[PDB]
Length: 45
Length: 222
Image (tube, rainbow over all chains, first blue to last red; front, side, top):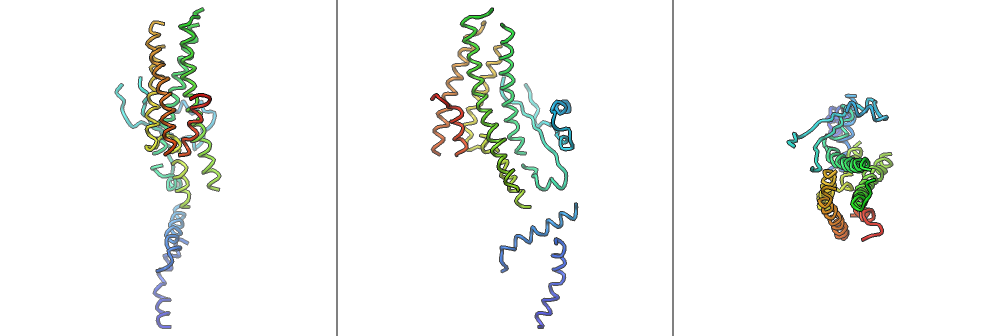
């Protein structure tokens, strides 16, 4: 629990960044990089 | 250009603008070269897809314009000779057969271009589309420059084309005071054309795009 309650709040600001465009398996790594730039591009249009 | 678009009978839309007919060189002074570009222009939400390098249209354009210089100059001598007509002799008829023999070679190399760079390469990239893919699909459509004999790999095939285009321009200069001076020119034309058929054949063993060329240049001959 103690580590979880830290991780549950140590990722709070990072979700916000992810909440804009809207090791680990690289099958999704490069996809996140483009899944955001599209949102950041529609914001200027 | 603003006088050209009026005679287009297709265009005069917001798309039709942004045709900056600019240049990229200052010519000093019979050849087959007249360097001149023609660049499209776009705005923000489309500029991010159509790359400012996909500059390669200007590469394939200066060739296609250079081709028109033949079918007009050659049309001139076909029209320049018409007013000469009473004057019927061996020197006359034997002269006009050269034009029909030189024109057909241009009207077949053009028919090739009008099949690869405008119709089959357009069949793809039209039934291919229907965000990252749009960049690569477009980078694969134009990469029109391969079937266009502009690639450095098949460059020797292109170098020989100038020898053909040059001799037709000289044929236009001599619009029968100097018949023999022209008879030697045509004989140089029949040699170079006969050399092209061998250099393309030798380059088959080493490109399915070039395969259709030999079927175009050769038909009931050797």
